[PDB]
Length: 303
Length: 73
Length: 65
Image 1 (cartoon, rainbow over the protein chains, first blue to last red):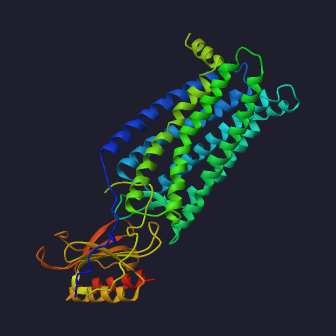
Image 2 (cartoon, rainbow over the protein chains, first blue to last red):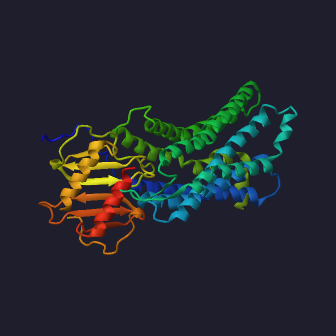
Image 3 (cartoon, rainbow over the protein chains, first blue to last red):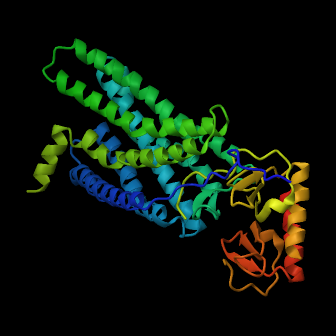
């Protein structure tokens, strides 16, 4: 008849804050507005004149559409972050499908642009360069692959009502949902980070190697642009994937699990999601408006 | 009530030393679901400290049943 | 206390996701039972009602699987 006492076997209760909520709302609204304006301007510049529509123009059009759809979906995500998912199951499914489809499409389009530049520079004089005039079919295939890879979100998502937390547009795959979610996370980290990252690194490394050996007067600017693109992609996507892998390891008990680490991982996940959302706004500047053609077009249109 | 994009179990480990039910005042049982793969039993102690019991261990069922029976009276 | 009124319409236990029991004491007079259902609603159940007692036992037995 002795009190059992407490020896760290206590429920780990999550910590809630409201400043982060207001900051998240402001950041999401700013990102929404910037992405909308930039993507609309890119689309208008490309579509105003049908003269000189090259492969890069098609790629940029597809990328702009993807980013515009992502930004258009953002506001409901911001509201959900504010007060959890109150909008119902059907909207959860549809919005998640749109968001993930556009995310996959954007990443794969960046990879395709990298391959296009590799072919256009490294193999400029060879006969392989002629194989880059299949932009329409390649873009259609990328969109189809994104739609295929986004199916699990559509099929296995609904509204989950928990006790410690507000309702969430989560996945409900049964009593064993955690393991299936961990497995399904393999697709975003393989066809979303690792494969595009390797393709981009290979292509841009060889492109830089060829450029450094040339004697043109414009080598420096192209090299700086390539470095900026690669660093932007890394800064945007590496932290989120690193934190996701850390969470996956923590759940599997490969790394020790404690309340402090869980709270830190949640905070890092939120911060890294906010950080990675900036790609929809930074793509138009990095890929489209850093070129003379688009700037001249923008100047001409305003006449 | 906050919001999170990762749902986790509420108990990391469980108390293992059997103890008399007289020290229990409040009980909570959470069925397994999307949030956690195992049922969770959390009990308040006499002094206010909270504990996580093992849902499948033998003595836990006895203790929970005795507490509920006594409270129901 | 944490409960005021209790539902008077019995419902199938299959919707009960979470259960909580608070014994009477200095804080209140009658033991309180709070159930969180699949649809997000929170209900307070009177321990003295037979249907409440049966539902609690059914939920407890199911949760032990």
